[PDB]
Image (cartoon, coloured by chain):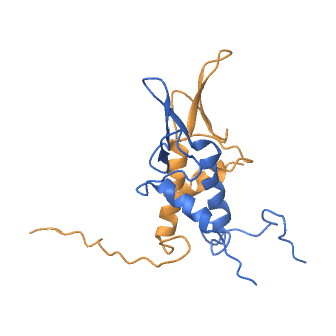
Chain colours: A blue, B orange
Amino acid sequence: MGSSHHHHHHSSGRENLYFQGMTDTAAEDVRKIATALLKTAIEIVSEEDGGAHNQCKLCGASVPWLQTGDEIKHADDCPVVIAKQILSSRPKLHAV
Amino acid sequence: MGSSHHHHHHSSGRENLYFQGMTDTAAEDVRKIATALLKTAIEIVSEEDGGAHNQCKLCGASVPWLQTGDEIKHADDCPVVIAKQILSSRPKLHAV
């Protein structure tokens, strides 16, 4: 029993909602593509003088490239930011 | 004598669920992310053994630099497949 202790979908079915079941399974795939943002989508745009700027290709992230970079600042007018918040919220298991 | 004057599509009352406006906007919000993460995360690779190629970040989609955009295959192992499914949501490509 148990099954899900280190698996990415045992099998499941299809033809129900947009994200397979979506009532539960939606979060897994959504955060996966959202993580791709940090994977390679985020990078520095080159300067004209001789340097760069730390910017998301929209507004999902932006800050002086040599400033922290850990909690990179977000402009919430961009749909890229919601993705960050989704994966930060995550499915919560409340137990003591 | 006349037809419409005010936009009654002003109804702003989406449920406060997991995926923000999870009822119909659920598909919208995620598609926003999928659309942005695709368009702004494509690197054009210049090859000395070939030429300039249009290749998406995770290699999940590749198209001639002439850019057709619509007709592009899918790397089945790459999470690009689900991203496409989300941002498209339209009956296209059977891909056997």
Residue lying at the far front of the rendered structure? A67
Q: Residue at x 59, y 48 (%)?
A: A37
Q: Which residue is drawn at 26% across and 73% down?
A: B8
Query: Where is residue B56, by image quadrant?
Result: top right
Q: Count of labels shown?
A: 0
Q: In which quarter of the image is the C terminus of chain A?
A: bottom right
Relative image position of residue A4 (x, y in whole percent): 83, 70
Q: In which quarter of the image is the N terminus of chain A?
A: bottom right
Q: Residue at x 48, y 41 (%)?
A: A64
The answer to whether residue B13 is above or below residue B66 is below
Task: From the viewer's side, name the closer residue of B80 and A49.
Answer: A49
Residue lying at the far bottom of the rendered structure? A96
Residue lying at the far right of the rendered structure? A1
Relative image position of residue B73 (x, y in whole percent): 64, 41
Relative image position of residue B95 (x, y in whole percent): 68, 48
Relative image position of residue B38 (x, y in whole percent): 55, 45
Q: Which residue is drawn at 82% across and 64% down?
A: A7
Residue lying at the far left of the rendered structure? B1
The answer to whether residue B89 is above or below residue A47 is below
The answer to whether residue B49 is above or below residue A88 is above
